[PDB]
Image (cartoon, coloured by chain):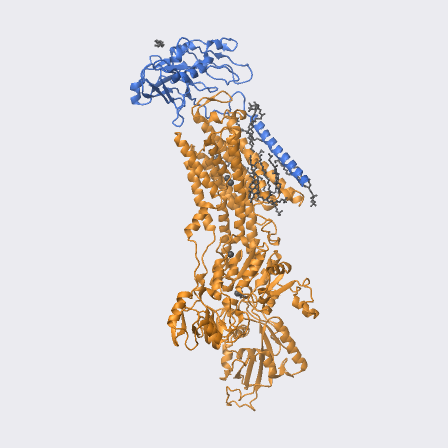
Chain colours: A blue, B orange
């Protein structure tokens, strides 16, 4: 009957409303136990990943220096990423602090609490990325056979990278360790036959060192420390075989930095570059 | 199909019709061309479907069509992905699992699907191999198959009748038509028209019936399948290919669930088309919908439940041939039961004996040890001696330590009954028969209806000749001039004759066959010891006898039958007796069992009481009715329907097997589930047409046991009430199992709906929900079949098949909407807890699935600004999926607890009374622990290890489910029929 229909609809309305209320109350009680400044857990993001800027789809780079449209996507992506790294957007001193040009110890800017207000970020200037900054070089190197990719370390709150001590033999002598303040980064060919065609490697870092300075760490969380500019490392090749596909691997060494076979980007690259004639 | 019976014709008309001759027969050419045209005299076996097609047809029944569509969609998705260079796999696994599920479900359904078989194999024991037929006036032995209609055949004693013949020459021929009437009483044969009905015409022999004694000659009229037993076999093999009530309920449940799944899939596929999704995403969503909305493990669980019940019933000597038949007994509304062999013991037994002008009652139980009916009274010694000495039956050899009622005896049925009585009440009559010498006289000639035996007493005191005689009571009385009442002998008083006659009439009224007894001592003054005796009955007198007593036989019911019938009638079942015996015996047995109560009274009895015409009495007053075969052969079906509807207690008498089939069909026209009990060939068509057929084990015949769905090995008729108990318990526990199975579909379906609509990362995968469907819920589904009865099961009325369904709308609504939604809510709470505690707040997960599942992006920014590689994102996804799985499991623990009852409370029913429930809970604990910390230590099948706190987030939601269900059942209990019983009870 119509009255029966009204009674059943009223019952279902109140029942579903009560269920929704219980669900929302449980969500609120759970959210009361998470902090808005630091994550409760870092199980999955504790070993930071390594990522390049051009953001290539199939882990491959195939372009022709002749046709502008062949490298237009990479050039536009690099411009889009590096637009925020221009010094024109870092001039304000209330929120930016000029940190020295020489690598130094990590900066502890207080503690993860609402007190002490916001944080100040060390400024990263494009001049340190020599001949891949876009200031006085067009196409960001994508002229005849001069590709360069900007390597970055994934942001993790409270993360202080620990560079490897030079006690154990790391690699061939780089003639400058500076371990306590620089996290080493090196790009090598994937296997033996790609080392003969990869060519020389040019690293452009802050202060001339080949790695990420530790003065920019730790990250504080986009709320305490917004407008944070992570350190960059432009890697340029300048010599590679035309019409050939070369697999190049970039690895970040450190005591705390980890690797994984399952995860291919945990401190490593699998990038392929092919330069057509 | 020939039915133009012509037993009215004389010999000459038979000759002209069939073109033969008694002296000659049929010529060889004539017989060969008959064998060519008419066909061999052999029951033609029916066409049967080979088992492999019966097995293959199971792969398209149930939920298997949806699973096949899902497997096809999985293959299409994989080929599309392979074209686009996607080695992710994860879909061949799903297709293989779906195909394996289809195969396993088909295997289980084939195991549950009937038994097929044919009845013809049972008739081979009766069909004769050869026959003595005459051709060209020569007596030759010819195989019965070669015999064809029209030829003259001669039948001796002790052999099966070759075919349906019309007797022309007979000499003391007595047949045993137990396959047509169910009665082993020898039926005499003649060469004259006796009855209009060919089944009682007395001048027709029947195919496969045995001739007990004598010679006969007849003209074959029907052969092969045109014979009466041929039609019986054709009917018993050509009917019964119909679904069972439990099969119909399961099919309706499948229809409801499949309709829900199809509707949801179609509507959400249309919405996905209307929301700019790629075809691959749409078909993946469709596969997830199909897998989530199908209860794969339920149809096998029902089979396992039925198998467990069948085993625990076969433990009680009740073999269940058809697995689907355990349920049917319990939804049965009408039990049409055979009289002889089923309700009665099929053995002639003395019931009443009359002397001293009083009626004594004798025990008739099969396992009786002794008899005590005022034995110390007078006249009992003379009655004992006359019963012992005046008998011809003898026990069979090899019977030293055999139970007395189970000892095989050679002799007449009446002689066997008296001999069993004497052995029981005296112990050893062999010594008594030996010590009392028997003169070589025992005239038991036909048309005499009496027999006498002269003996000499072994007692030295008397030492006088004795003439004991028994026979028809009227002949005994007319030869009697005195009666022995308490030692001394009264004259033939008018009052004594009146008492004799009224005892005769009442004993006949109880449907019993009386036998009169009388003895006459011969004084030695007139008959010396050496006096010669002659068989001519002229050397000794046969008059002026003394009547001692009068005994009657009943063929009594089994000991457990009356109580079982009373319980069945108290359980709301209507018992009908359909028998081939005479109406008087059937009515007496019905009154003695409980089919007709003592107070209930039929039309004929009302007419006798009021002395008015039988047409004058209104049939509304009569509460019982006895219908003979003739009253039913000319009954229009509407009249039969009204007869069944009006009268609560009905007895059918002198019914042919076709009439039994007619009665069963007419009872099924009233939308009633019928059960048939029988132990004879004539019950096979009824035992097949019935929804469940029950046959006796020891007393039963091969045809009945082949045509039945259940066989009682010890012939304990009391097993029917236990069967009804088990069937009703099965129905209730099946409701519980179906609710518990359907409740977990919604927690598996809601994540995919939310994933499509709000674009969250996938809360759970398809293999994960398959693990719920196949691994965790099966043992609790079996456990819910061990729940004890909530209320008085055997006091309810039988369920209405059309009105009451196993899966109604209330159960489906409660399982999908009231429960299931709560489980989805708890699982989503756990999922949001897992995601938020690692960096992704609940509001940051809206419409993130496109960037979440992009292998190109490896710097996804969460709420805190951290950047996540693709593999870390999918590892977090697997963690959330495993946690959602665990939440579903725990809320299913709660739902098992709340589904243990339907109207009661867990406080009343008991938490630990059902240990299989706790076995199921422990099994889920073990299975989840393995699936989380084994498989998952290596990330596989979207399983990862879980933190300790993710195992207990959904426990409060389980407690909430339990509290809500307890409140619902409490309000159902408090106010019955108060809009809460009508809407919330399932
Ligand atoms: C039966 C099956 C049921 C399944 C249920 C699935 C539900 C899926 C919905 C999930 C969203 C839940 C959000 C609840 C969040 C808490 C409530 C609240 O108070 O949150 C206010 C939010 C901020 O919370 P936070 O996450 O920042 O807290 C972070 C924690 N702390 C505060 C500590 C930092 O305010 C904000 O910033 C955002 C303000 C604007 C929000 C716009 C949302 C528009 C989304 C629409 C999609 C709706 C789809 C519905 C589909 C139904 C299908 C049946
Ligand atoms: C986004 C999508 C989410 C999907 C969630 C799950 C959706 C499905 C859930 C429940 C649907 C159950 C369908 C059951 C169908 C039964 C089929 C059938 O065989 O029918 C036979 C019955 C016989 O009736 P009877 O004589 O036994 O009744 C006697 C009543 N007495 C006693 C008061 C007189 O016929 C009837 O009952 C009439 C049946 C009328 C049904 C009308 C439609 C009901 C469906 C409502 C669902 C709407 C969507 C809900 C989504 C919620 C999202 C929050
Ligand atoms: C997460 C996964 C799912 C978790 C779900 C949990 C649901 C709650 C389970 C509650 C189990 C209760 C145990 C229980 O009821 O056992 C029943 C027995 C015997 O019953 P009876 O002889 O009275 O029946 C008389 C029968 N007739 C009336 C016919 C004579 O009694 C006993 O063993 C001793 C208990 C006596 C009755 C209760 C006395 C008060 C105790 C309350 C503690 C439990 C309820 C409160 C906590 C709920 C959870 C927060
Ligand atoms: C009806 C209630 C009574 C019936 C249930 C009784 C359950 C009894 C079971 C107890 C076992 C507790 C689990 C094992 C022990 C706790 C483990 C644990 O550590 O669990 C804590 C989590 C949050 O971890 P945390 O932030 O302390 O870790 C900080 C880590 N550090 C310091 C490195 C940043 O607590 C959470 O998730 C809280 C989750 C809140 C949402 C749950 C539903 C609430 C609704 C009501
Ligand atoms: C907090 C933990 C979870 C709590 C769950 C609570 C479940 C129970 C909720 C409501 C049922 C209350 C009524 C019980 C008795 C009904 C008597 C009756 O319906 O009377 C009927 C008229 O009533 C009405 O029109 C109103 C019907 C009841 C409306 C209840 C309120 C609306 C719906 C509430 C449901 C909320 C559920 C929320 C759950 C959220 C998730 C956990 C007719 O009575 P009559 O004349 O035939 O009397 C019979 C006479 N005689 C007894 C002698 C035979
Ligand atoms: C919340 C909204 C979006 C969806 C829920 C709709 C619910 C409340 C409505 C829509 C159709 C309704 C159902 C229509 C038919 C029946 C069958 C009847 O025998 C009992 C009532 C019942 C079961 C109704 C219950 C309430 C009902 C299910
Ligand atoms: C909003 C959406 C989810 C509502 C969907 C309601 C659908 C799934 C429900 C509501 C009514 C239901 C139907 C009601 C009647 C019948 C006839 C029966 O012989 C088979 C089941 C069938 C065909 C049901 C199938 C499922 C059904 C169609
Ligand atoms: C009513 C409540 C208790 C029901 C909840 C059952 C929970 C608490 C039980 C059931 C299964 C159990 C888990 C099974 C697996 C593991 C992994 C092992 O390495 C640590 C113990 C741990 C984590 C167990 C903790 C306790 C546990 C989660
Ligand atoms: C790129 O920059 C380096 C900086 O030392 C410079 O030496 C080199 O010539 C440049 N390459 C060209 C050809 O632009
Ligand atoms: F003895 Al019957 F049907 F009457 F088997
Ligand atoms: K399911
Ligand atoms: K049957
Ligand atoms: K299920
Ligand atoms: Mg019988």
Which quarter of the figure has residue B553? bottom right
Q: Is residue B70 visible?
A: yes
Q: Residue at x 54, y 43 (%)?
A: B256
Q: Is residue A1 above or below residue B202?
A: above
Q: Is residue B954 visible?
A: no
Residue B359, x across and y down, in percent: 63, 73
Which quarter of the figure has residue B378? bottom right
Q: Nearer the viewer, residue B297 or B418?
A: B297
Q: Nearer the viewer, residue A209 or B306?
A: B306
Residue A224, x across and y down, in percent: 52, 16
Q: Is residue B814 above or below residue B133?
A: above
Extreme residue toward the front, this view: B16
Q: Is residue B684 above or below residue A224?
A: below
Q: Nearer the viewer, residue A93 or B277?
A: B277
What is the quadrant of the C terminus of chain B in the image? top right
B436 horizontally vs A165: left or right = right
B206 horizontally vs B973: left or right = left
Q: Quadrant of ligand 6?
A: top right
Residue B895, x across and y down, in percent: 56, 40
Q: Residue at x 53, y 41 (%)?
A: B259
């Amino acid at each position: 009957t119509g009255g029966s229909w009204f009674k059943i609809l009223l019952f279902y309305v109140i029942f579903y409303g009560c269920l929704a209320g219980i669900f929302i109350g449980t969500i609120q009680v759970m959210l009361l136990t998470i902090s808005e400044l630091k994550p409760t857990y870092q199980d999955r993001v504790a070993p930071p990943g390594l990522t390049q800027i051009p953001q290539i789809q199939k882990t491959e780079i195939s372009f022709r220096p002749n046709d502008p449209k062949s490298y237009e996507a990479y050039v536009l992506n690099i411009i889009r990423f590096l637009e925020k790294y221009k010094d024109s957007a870092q001039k304000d001193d209330m929120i930016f602090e000029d940190c020295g040009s020489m690598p130094s110890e990590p900066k502890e800017r207080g503690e993860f609490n609402h007190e002490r207000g916001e944080r100040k970020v060390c400024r990263f200037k494009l001049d340190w990325l020599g001949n891949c900054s876009g200031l006085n070089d067009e196409s960001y190197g994508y002229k005849e056979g001069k590709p360069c990719i900007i390597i970055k370390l994934n942001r993790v709150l409270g993360f202080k990278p620990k560079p490897p001590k030079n006690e154990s033999l790391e690699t061939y002598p780089l003639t400058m360790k500076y371990n306590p303040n620089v996290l080493p980064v090196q790009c090598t060919g994937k296997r033996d036959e790609d080392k003969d065609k990869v060519g020389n490697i040019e690293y452009f870092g802050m202060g001339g060192f080949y790695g990420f300075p530790l003065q920019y760490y730790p990250y504080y969380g986009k709320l305490l420390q917004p407008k944070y500019l992570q350190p960059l490392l432009a890697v340029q090749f300048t010599n590679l075989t035309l019409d050939t596909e070369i697999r190049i691997e970039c690895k970040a060494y450190g005591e705390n930095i980890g690797y994984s076979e399952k995860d291919r980007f945990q401190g490593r690259f699998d990038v392929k570059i092919e330069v057509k004639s | 199909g020939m039915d133009l019976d012509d037993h009215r014709l004389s010999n000459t008309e038979l000759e002209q019709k069939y073109g033969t001759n008694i002296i000659q027969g049929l010529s060889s050419v004539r017989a060969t061309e008959l064998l060519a045209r008419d066909g061999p005299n052999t029951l033609t076996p029916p066409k049967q479907t080979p088992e492999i097609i019966k097995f293959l047809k199971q792969m398209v029944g149930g939920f298997s069509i949806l699973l096949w569509i899902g497997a096809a969609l999985c293959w299409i998705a994989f080929v599309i992905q392979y074209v686009n260079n996607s080695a992710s796999l994860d879909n061949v696994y799903l297709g293989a699992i779906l195909v394996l599920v289809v195969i396993l479900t088909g295997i289980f359904a084939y195991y549950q699907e009937a038994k097929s078989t044919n009845i013809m194999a049972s008739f081979s024991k009766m069909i004769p191999q050869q026959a003595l037929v005459i051709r060209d006036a020569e007596k030759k032995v010819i195989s019965a198959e070669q015999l064809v209609v029209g030829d003259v055949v001669e039948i001796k004693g002790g052999d099966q009748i070759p075919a349906d013949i019309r007797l022309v020459f007979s000499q003391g021929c007595k047949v045993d038509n137990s396959s047509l009437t169910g009665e082993s009483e020898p039926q005499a044969r003649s060469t004259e028209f006796t009855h209009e009905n060919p089944l009682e015409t007395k001048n027709i022999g029947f195919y496969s019936t045995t001739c007990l004694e004598g010679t006969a000659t007849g003209i074959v009229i029907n052969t092969g399948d045109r014979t009466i037993i041929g039609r019986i076999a054709s009917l018993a093999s050509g009917v019964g290919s119909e679904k069972t009530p439990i099969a119909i309920e399961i099919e309706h449940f499948v229809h409801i669930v499949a309709g829900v799944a199809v509707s949801i899939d179609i509507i959400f596929f249309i919405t996905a088309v209307c929301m700019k999704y790629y075809v691959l995403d749409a078909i993946i969503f469709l596969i997830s919908i199909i897998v989530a909305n199908v209860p794969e493990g339920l149809l096998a669980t029902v089979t396992v439940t039925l198998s467990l019940t069948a085993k625990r019933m076969a433990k009680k000597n009740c073999l269940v041939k058809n697995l689907e038949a355990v349920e049917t007994l319990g939804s049965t509304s009408i039990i049409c039961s055979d009289k002889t062999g089923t309700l009665t013991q099929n053995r002639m037994t003395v019931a009443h004996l009359w002397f001293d002008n009083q009626i004594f009652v004798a025990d008739t139980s099969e396992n009786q040890t002794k008899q005590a009916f005022d034995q110390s009274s007078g006249t009992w010694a003379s009655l004992s001696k006359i019963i012992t000495l005046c008998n011809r039956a003898e026990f069979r050899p090899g019977q030293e330590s055999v139970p007395i009622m189970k000892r095989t005896v050679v002799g007449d049925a009446s002689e066997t009954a008296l001999l069993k009585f004497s052995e029981v009440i005296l112990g050893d009559v062999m010594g008594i028969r030996k010590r009392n010498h028997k003169v070589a006289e025992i005239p038991f000639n036909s048309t005499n209806k009496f027999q006498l035996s002269i003996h000499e007493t072994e007692d030295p005191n008397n030492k006088r000749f004795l003439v004991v005689m028994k026979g028809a009571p009227e002949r005994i009385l007319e030869k009697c001039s005195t009666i022995m009442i308490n030692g001394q002998e009264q004259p033939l008083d008018k009052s004594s004759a009146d008492s004799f006659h009224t005892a005769y009439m009442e004993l006949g009224g109880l449907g019993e066959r009386v036998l009169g007894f009388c003895h006459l001592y011969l004084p030695a003054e007139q008959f010396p010891q050496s006096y010669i005796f002659d068989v001519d009955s002229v050397n000794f007198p046969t008059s002026n006898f003394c009547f001692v007593g009068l005994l009657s036989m009943i063929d009594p019911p089994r000991s457990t039958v009356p109580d079982a019938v009373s319980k069945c009638r108290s359980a709301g079942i209507k018992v009908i007796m359909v028998t081939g015996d005479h109406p008087i015996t059937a009515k007496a047995i019905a009154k003695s069992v409980g089919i007709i109560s003592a107070n209930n009274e039929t039309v004929e009895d009302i007419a006798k009481r009021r002395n008015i015409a039988v047409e004058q009495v209104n049939k509304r007053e009569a509460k019982a009715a006895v219908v003979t075969g003739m009253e039913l052969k000319d009954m229009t079906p509407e009249q039969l329907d009204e007869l069944l509807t009006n009268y609560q207690e009905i007895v059918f008498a002198r019914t042919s097997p076709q009439q039994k089939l007619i009665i069963v069909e007419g009872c099924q026209r009233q939308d009633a589930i019928v059960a048939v009990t029988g132990d004879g060939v004539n019950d096979s068509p009824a035992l097949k047409k019935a929804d469940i057929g029950i046959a006796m084990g020891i007393a039963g015949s091969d045809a009945a046991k082949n045509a039945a769905d259940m066989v009682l090995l010890d012939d304990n008729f009391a097993s029917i009430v236990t069967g009804v108990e088990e069937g009703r318990l099965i129905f209730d526990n099946l409701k519980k199992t179906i609710a518990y199975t359907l409740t977990s579909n919604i927690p598996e379906l809601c994540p995919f709906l939310i994933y499509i609509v709000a674009g969250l990362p996938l809360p759970i995968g398809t293999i994960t929900i398959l693990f719920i469907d196949l691994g965790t819920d099966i043992i609790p589904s079996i456990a819910l079949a061990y729940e004890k009865a909530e209320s008085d099961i055997m006091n309810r009325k039988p369920r209405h098949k059309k009105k009451d369904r196993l899966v109604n709308t209330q159960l489906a609504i409660y399982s999908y909407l009231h429960i299931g939604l709560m489980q989805a809510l708890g699982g989503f709470l756990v999922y949001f807890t897992v995601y938020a505690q690692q960096g992704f707040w609940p509001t940051s997960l809206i419409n993130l699935r496109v960037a979440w599942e992009t292998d190109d992006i490896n710097d996804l920014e969460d709420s805190y600004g951290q950047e996540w590689t693709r593999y870390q994102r999918k590892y977090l996804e697997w963690t959330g999926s495993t946690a959602f799985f665990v939440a579903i499991m725990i809320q299913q623990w709660a739902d098992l607890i709340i589904c243990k009852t339907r109207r009661n409370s867990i406080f009343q029913q008991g938490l630990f009374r059902n240990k299989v429930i706790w076995v199921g809970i422990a099994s889920q604990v073990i299975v989840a622990l393995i699936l989380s910390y084994g498989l998952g230590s290596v990330p596989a099948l979207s399983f990862t290890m879980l933190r300790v706190q993710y195992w207990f987030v959904a426990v409060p939601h389980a407690i909430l489910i339990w509290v809500y269900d307890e409140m619902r059942k409490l309000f159902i209990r408090l106010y019955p029929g108060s809009w809460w019983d009508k809407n919330m009870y399932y």
